[PDB]
Amino acid sequence: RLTELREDIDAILEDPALEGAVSGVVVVDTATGEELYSRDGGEQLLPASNMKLFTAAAALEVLGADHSFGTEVAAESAPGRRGEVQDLYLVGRGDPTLSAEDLDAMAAEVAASGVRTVRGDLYADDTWFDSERLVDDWWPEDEPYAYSAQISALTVAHGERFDTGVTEVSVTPAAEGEPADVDLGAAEGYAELDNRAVTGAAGSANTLVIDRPVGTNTIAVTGSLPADAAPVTALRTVDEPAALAGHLFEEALESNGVTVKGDVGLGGVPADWQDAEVLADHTSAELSEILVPFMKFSNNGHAEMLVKSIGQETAGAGTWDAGLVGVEEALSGLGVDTAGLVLNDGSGLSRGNLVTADTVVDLLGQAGSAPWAQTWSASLPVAGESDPFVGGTLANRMRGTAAEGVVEAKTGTMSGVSALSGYVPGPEGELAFSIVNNGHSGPAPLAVQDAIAVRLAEYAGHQAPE
Ligand SMILES: *[B-](O)(O)[C@@H](C)NS(C)(=O)=O
Ligand SMILES: [Mg+2]
Ligand SMILES: [Mg+2]
Image 1 (cartoon, rainbow, N blue to C red):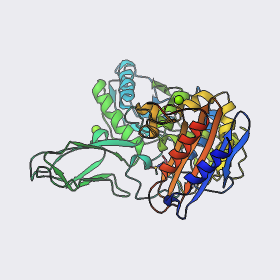
Image 2: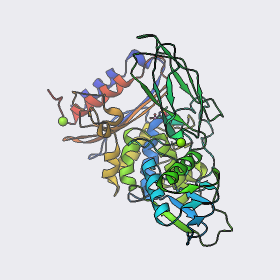
Image 3: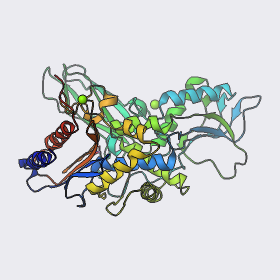
């Protein structure tokens, strides 16, 4: 034993997929502190979504398991007799889990506090973070999509997954030759529609494109949708998230019995306002439980929002420059050697990132003994588990294997980058492992990742369900 593990993993790393790829592979037995397996442990590689490990362990350190985010709506005075306020300010403070149901409940409170007429304009105050929406090196072709959604203090989160800065577009088909019905979701009335899509014949080619062209707030829909096709739904981003949350809170007040007389725009509570009257407040879930949808489904928006939030705790600045340092700081303070690291964002979306595998293993050992260990461990995706909120990105992976409901790891994935790091808690020692793969030519070496992980599940003393 022990040497067998070497041959097994050595052989797994011979696949034709590893033509001209660099692969960092580090396995350590937490209990003994034994270096089970190490190959290119110090080599510097792009982590992709394994950067979320760092951002998450750091959000814990800096923000606390119990940290919650609050939204506030302000006017310059309380409503009196006539139930009239002037300008109304929707003031967000870094809430990643902010639904339209919450804006309703805040619009409910605005009415019940006595406002009936917002005589001035309704304003969106997301000044809590900087107005820098996208990291330096993200791609303009990524912009339209949930993972490249803009970063704001005031964002509307969709679904129970809390996908920020996006509206769900719906394209139901109609009759052959007729244009299809496009439904812009929450951003109805905020975003432009450029519907050029047509309903095609029955069982015909599906070539439907839902896009938002760069630097525009226009949802340009193209292509064709069959008459028989299952109605389509897809997440697209808006320009200026808070301006949408503005528009949506607009609708809420109109609904809750409040006439709004002026325009909706971006704006920060003016400095001349002395003693503001806060008409509605809200409170998110505690971070620890926000970690779940964030880590399970690999939420980018959450990652960056948390960073910039980290930049507010330590520096008073909703800024990447501010939070990234703070992140690096916390991990250092966690017992982590930051020699190998290079941080250009929270999510791992930036190609400006670098990690080594020894560094990830380093992180994992440290975080494991942290007073926040178990909610961190929990937030991580679990192998082969049908439940999305438990499976995460490992739901359809390693099913019916020694790694099923066992391996707690996190995945990292983008063009020519693939990664798996985490815990294999076995009877023969809680294993922590990292596998980082860069610059492969053909398919994703997900098979080589699972293979390693399943074998490690077996070494730990597990066996495949039958
Ligand atoms: B992560 O889940 O690898 C994330 C960065 N992936 S991506 C490229 O935004 O889809
Ligand atoms: Mg609307
Ligand atoms: Mg088992």
